[PDB]
Image (cartoon, coloured by chain):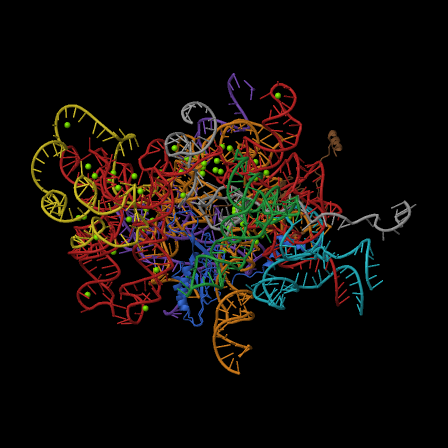
Chain colours: A blue, B brown, C green, D red, E cyan, G yellow, H purple, I orange
Amino acid sequence: KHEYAPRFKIVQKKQKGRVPVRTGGSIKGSTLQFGKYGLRLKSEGIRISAQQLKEADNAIMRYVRPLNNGHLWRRLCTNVAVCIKGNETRMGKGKGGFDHWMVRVPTGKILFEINGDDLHEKVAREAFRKAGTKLPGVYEFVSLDSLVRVGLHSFKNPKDDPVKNFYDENAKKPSKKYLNILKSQEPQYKLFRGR
Amino acid sequence: SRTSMKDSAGRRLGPKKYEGQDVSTGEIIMRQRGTKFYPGENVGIGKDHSIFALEPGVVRYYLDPFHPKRKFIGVALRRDLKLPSPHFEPTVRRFGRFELTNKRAAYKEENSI
RNA sequence: GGCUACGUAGCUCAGUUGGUAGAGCACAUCACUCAUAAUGAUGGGGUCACAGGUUCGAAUCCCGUCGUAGCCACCA
RNA sequence: GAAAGAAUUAAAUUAAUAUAAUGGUAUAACUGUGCGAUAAUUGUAACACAAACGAGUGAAACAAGUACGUAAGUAUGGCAUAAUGAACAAAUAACACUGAUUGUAAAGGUUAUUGAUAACGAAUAAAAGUUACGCUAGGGAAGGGUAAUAUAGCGAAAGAGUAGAUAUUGUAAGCUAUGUUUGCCACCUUCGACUCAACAUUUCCUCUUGGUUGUAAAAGCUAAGAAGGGUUUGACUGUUCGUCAAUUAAAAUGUUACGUGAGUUGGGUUAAAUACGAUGUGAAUCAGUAUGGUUCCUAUCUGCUGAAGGAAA
RNA sequence: AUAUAUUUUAGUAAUAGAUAAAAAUAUGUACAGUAAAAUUGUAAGGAAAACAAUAAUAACUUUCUC
RNA sequence: CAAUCUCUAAUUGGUAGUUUUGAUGGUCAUUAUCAGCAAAAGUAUCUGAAUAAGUCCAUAAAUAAAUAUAUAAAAUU
RNA sequence: AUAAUUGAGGUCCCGCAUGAAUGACGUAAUGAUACAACAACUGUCUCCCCUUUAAGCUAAGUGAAAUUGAAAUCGUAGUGA
RNA sequence: AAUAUUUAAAAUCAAAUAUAUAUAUAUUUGUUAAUAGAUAAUAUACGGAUCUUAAUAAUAAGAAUUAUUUAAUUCCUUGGAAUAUUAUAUUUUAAAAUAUAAAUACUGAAUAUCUAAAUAUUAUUAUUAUA
RNA sequence: UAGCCUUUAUAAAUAAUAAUUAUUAUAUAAUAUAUUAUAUAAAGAAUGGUACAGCAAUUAAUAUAUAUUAGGGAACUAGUUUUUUAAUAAUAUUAAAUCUCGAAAUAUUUAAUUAUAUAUAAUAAAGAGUCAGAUUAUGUGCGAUAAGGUAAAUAAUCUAAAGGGAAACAGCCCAGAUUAAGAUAUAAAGUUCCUAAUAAAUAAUAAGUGAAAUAAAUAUUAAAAU
Ligand SMILES: [Mg+2]
Ligand SMILES: [Mg+2]
Ligand SMILES: [Mg+2]
Ligand SMILES: [Mg+2]
Ligand SMILES: [Mg+2]
Ligand SMILES: [Mg+2]
Ligand SMILES: [Mg+2]
Ligand SMILES: [Mg+2]
Ligand SMILES: [Mg+2]
Ligand SMILES: [Mg+2]
Ligand SMILES: [Mg+2]
Ligand SMILES: [Mg+2]
Ligand SMILES: [Mg+2]
Ligand SMILES: [Mg+2]
Ligand SMILES: [Mg+2]
Ligand SMILES: [Mg+2]
Ligand SMILES: [Mg+2]
Ligand SMILES: [Mg+2]
Ligand SMILES: [Mg+2]
Ligand SMILES: [Mg+2]
Ligand SMILES: [Mg+2]
Ligand SMILES: [Mg+2]
Ligand SMILES: [Mg+2]
Ligand SMILES: [Mg+2]
Ligand SMILES: [Mg+2]
Ligand SMILES: [Mg+2]
Ligand SMILES: [Mg+2]
Ligand SMILES: [Mg+2]
Ligand SMILES: [Mg+2]
Ligand SMILES: [Mg+2]
Ligand SMILES: [Mg+2]
Ligand SMILES: [Mg+2]
Ligand SMILES: [Mg+2]
Ligand SMILES: [Mg+2]
Ligand SMILES: [Mg+2]
Ligand SMILES: [Mg+2]
Ligand SMILES: [Mg+2]
Ligand SMILES: [Mg+2]
Ligand SMILES: [Mg+2]
Ligand SMILES: [Mg+2]
Ligand SMILES: [Mg+2]
Ligand SMILES: [Mg+2]
Ligand SMILES: [Mg+2]
Ligand SMILES: [Mg+2]
Ligand SMILES: [Mg+2]
Ligand SMILES: [Mg+2]
Ligand SMILES: [Mg+2]
Ligand SMILES: [Mg+2]
Ligand SMILES: [Mg+2]
Ligand SMILES: [Mg+2]
Ligand SMILES: [Mg+2]
Ligand SMILES: [Mg+2]
Ligand SMILES: [Mg+2]
């Protein structure tokens, strides 16, 4: 509903920033969560405007609405407010006025997701290709068995990466603050703190 | 047009004296906005929460179990002392005065009340 | 920072050189006219500008600052 | 087993903080309450932080006095970081320091206090415009870059096309090229006409060819090859352009310092004169209108057009 | 029971608790305490007036008791 | 009266000497807070600010609260 | 009006932003003023051609000028204050 | 063969290094190409020539592009050893055997060294005449 | 005026610059469950909140044949169910200049030790010049993730630096000219010729692709792996 037009109460101008190249191997929003088939970015990290996203959504919908129990999950919201000065105006003299909403999209991230009752995968693939024709990146069809993109030419299965109880790890190799707290909890300090 | 071209300078609010550093009485160990560091052993605190040394010694940053979730800056009277000092041991104190070996000076001091 | 002189009724204005709550004025009802209205008579509200003293007796004198613009000073 | 107390643990600083925002604050800096109303005191302040100077900030300690607290102690205004202004010249007090012959005085000094210089390190107590009649010293304290726009193309194809997205058409969004427009940058300080044109091809005509339920024929439409040859004369306007008239096989689009003023012109743009409308108190002014109105050059080199001499044939 | 005299009371006014997030003295000091939101309710009361209630007691001290 | 000399006041582009900030098409110039600021500190531009400041708060809730009531004392009665 | 007129004249009046001695309006005459039309004329032009004289050119004599860091001073593309 | 993905060393396998060590653990490395798309104005414009190899047939050429490498090739632990190569000499019948060598790729600065000269300073000397 | 530069000097002078040690844990050995030594591992005394990472709280975004709160319809005789409309909850998934509960490296930075002394700091007395900067790389603000643009941050070079390379070249890659000499090591860059110097190995390309200034989506044709 509000993914292409956030309702920040205090509307305000924003700096340009940069699209996060996720050097640490994030895989956040790079996985199929809601649907069966999806459309992910394949190229270098890119900014997608609100209008472009809307058009992609519309393109996808043409295939989704005919389906029985058809659904489209829009995975990303255009949260960054972009202002622009005109091409007509000189440089300097303040910042330009609000123009459009935009989203910073890392390399591996999923944009859309679909799942119908009577949805064959070929149709879904076609729809997602047609959606990609309207967006500024280069995109890729992603199924539930197809594995998570991280880099431009690199891949990963989330099933592989290890599970860890971090409290236990902390206890094993404790910080100074934690040790101080533990000492405080002990009786030769707790009795004589005198509050 | 109307531009937002106005800002105060930076308040120089780092630590002004570091761990293991020799100090003198009066010297500022920390400038800060509110007690990020609390005044520890042999150390005072000012109006602007500025930690300053009460005695000559060695600046030490530490945690104390009595005050968990609070960082401290204190001044150890020597380099030998671990400055979160043992609680039930006697306080390491500085006399900090000198006897008036000079006779006249001693006499003057005796006279003065 | 000091010094003035003015601020009655909803409107306009008296009154002022002390022993007064007065006047038309626009406003609502009767009156008169064929039927309007001009004209004739009904009444209307004032802490006599916030607020204290001297004469049994001051709206008027004296006397605190509200207020309105002045005036002086200081203006390096 | 029960009651009461002491409390501890968890959570919380999201409330509250005189006031912005940030940091801090429950051990509370927040809140309530007694006393008080004192420390919103007086002389010396080292040493640090910050820092060009001028200033600014934290502050141990020594001495005088005060308030609260059983005491320990705490208080030199406010949880902190804004809340401000130099000298000079005046003004008011206190000080007992100087007292221009001596004594008084005046006047100056010390100490405390006063009002502003917001263009806010404050030039004076006190200062706005105009010039196309202008002058001097200097500085540059279309080309180049860019490609948002513009022009052209490509991919995908919603949708028109009597039916069929792709004969022809092709929304909004996607990917490029160009440096032909309008911009942006600031390295770098004249429009049109005439004359002669050279180059490009993104081809307007002519030649070859693919597609065209939308190629029966004929006219077309669209696309590929193709730059050999060719591609206008008049009325209006300074105009390029545009409107129209009459033609043409066609009347293509650019580049060349938007080719070409040491080749011509000077209608536009342009200074001195003048008037009009508007603006201004005015001098005068204008992304205004109108009449008038100033540059010249024998060619040294390059280059090109012709013509000789010398030469190694 | 009634008369006079001399007095006394009635000026009728909130805090009764070291009060603790209604409002009020914004700097000192001493002592003490904890806010807010949300939720469940309740006369007018309704989304929005007020009041109530809403985390855990192991160990410790004292008291009574099987 | 008026004229002249000396003093004093009103008026003046009549006339003379000067001036017309730095940054911009009325707005910004001093101070504080955060971001920009890249985990010390500092850090700019006609950068973004729900930006904020030229302050505000004091002489006050007092007085009374132990020798007392007739008579007699004054070792506290 | 012209084959065709952003010019000229006539007329209309949302006069962006006319107006009465900063005069208003309509005429006769005048004007090397400015704009437009008709006639006549023409080398202005279609479209240039021929001729004449003075230069230009050559020989003799006399003899400048601006300019000039030094020059043994080609094209193209690239580069580069 | 057919259909549909992916173009990957994360997982997986293989190979190598390091810790106890015939194994385990940890680390490191290994996963497409071509063409079209393609484009303006003085003149082709990798700096230019030019570069993709070919038997017969050479004492002889065969990227001068892209990617990963080496300094002849293979094991052992920069070094040695073996292997063939190449060149040469000797001996024997243009070949065979023996042995010697080459294997340190090279170019390259006004860098460094060496080689000499100068000045200045520091520290030692020698000779000659604040010695 | 300070910053940076120069000259002359001063010491009860190393205060300067660089690194190490400093910590945590494990195993082994020796003393009294602790201490010391040895070895190994760990981005390893103190200070920090950027990258990264994350969705906690704040600010934002999405989904539920899930639950609650009411509303709009709807079927039988006001009660009830369903298809729902918003809010709240629950669960799952997401991001931000002014969010950071996790969190680097670089950084700031302290003592002693070692190494630099033909070297540094500090102080004293004196002289300046400079206050138009440029480019390259990285991280940003503005611009349009445009500019040989603009604004600052860090480093280097140019400025003021000749020499080799990058065709030519202020700022790029090497390297700092006291004067020569030219044997030896070389740097960056090169070794068919122009032009100083070359031979190999294994793959791939056939397009002159390319050969020192890499042009995109997309299309076609192959090639591997599943
Ligand atoms: Mg992120
Ligand atoms: Mg700040
Ligand atoms: Mg406060
Ligand atoms: Mg706060
Ligand atoms: Mg400092
Ligand atoms: Mg100073
Ligand atoms: Mg306080
Ligand atoms: Mg003055
Ligand atoms: Mg005298
Ligand atoms: Mg000024
Ligand atoms: Mg100033
Ligand atoms: Mg000034
Ligand atoms: Mg002035
Ligand atoms: Mg004029
Ligand atoms: Mg250009
Ligand atoms: Mg159709
Ligand atoms: Mg379109
Ligand atoms: Mg036909
Ligand atoms: Mg063509
Ligand atoms: Mg021909
Ligand atoms: Mg004509
Ligand atoms: Mg031109
Ligand atoms: Mg010319
Ligand atoms: Mg010329
Ligand atoms: Mg004339
Ligand atoms: Mg004048
Ligand atoms: Mg911060
Ligand atoms: Mg910062
Ligand atoms: Mg930093
Ligand atoms: Mg910082
Ligand atoms: Mg006409
Ligand atoms: Mg004409
Ligand atoms: Mg007039
Ligand atoms: Mg006239
Ligand atoms: Mg005349
Ligand atoms: Mg002659
Ligand atoms: Mg040059
Ligand atoms: Mg691996
Ligand atoms: Mg070319
Ligand atoms: Mg080359
Ligand atoms: Mg040398
Ligand atoms: Mg100086
Ligand atoms: Mg040292
Ligand atoms: Mg930040
Ligand atoms: Mg944290
Ligand atoms: Mg400057
Ligand atoms: Mg620049
Ligand atoms: Mg210079
Ligand atoms: Mg150089
Ligand atoms: Mg240098
Ligand atoms: Mg040198
Ligand atoms: Mg080529
Ligand atoms: Mg090239």
Q: Residue at x 41, y 51 (%)?
A: A85
Judging depth in this view, the residue of I220 and I102 nearest the camera is: I102
Residue I186 image point, x, y percent: 43, 41
Q: Residue at x 44, y 50 (%)?
A: A95
Q: Quadrant of ligand 17?
A: bottom left
Give the quarter of the figure containing the C terminus of chain B. Answer: top right
Side of C74 where G21 appears, left or right:
left
Specify the quadrant of the image occupied by residue G66.
Answer: top left
Judging depth in this view, the residue of D47 and H120 nearest the camera is: D47
Q: Is residue B25 above or below residue A54?
A: above
Q: Residue at x 71, y 35 (%)?
A: B98
Q: Residue at x 45, y 48 (%)?
A: B2
Residue A3 image point, x, y percent: 46, 61
Total numbered labels placed on residues in the image: 0
Residue A33 image point, x, y percent: 49, 65
- Residue A28 visible in this rendered orientation of the protein: no
Side of I81 where I147 appears, left or right:
left
Judging depth in this view, the residue of D167 and E34 nearest the camera is: E34
Q: Is residue G44 above or below residue D251?
A: above
Residue I185 image point, x, y percent: 44, 40
Q: Is residue D7 above or below residue E26?
A: below
- Residue B26 visible in this rendered orientation of the protein: yes
Side of C7 where E13 appears, left or right:
right
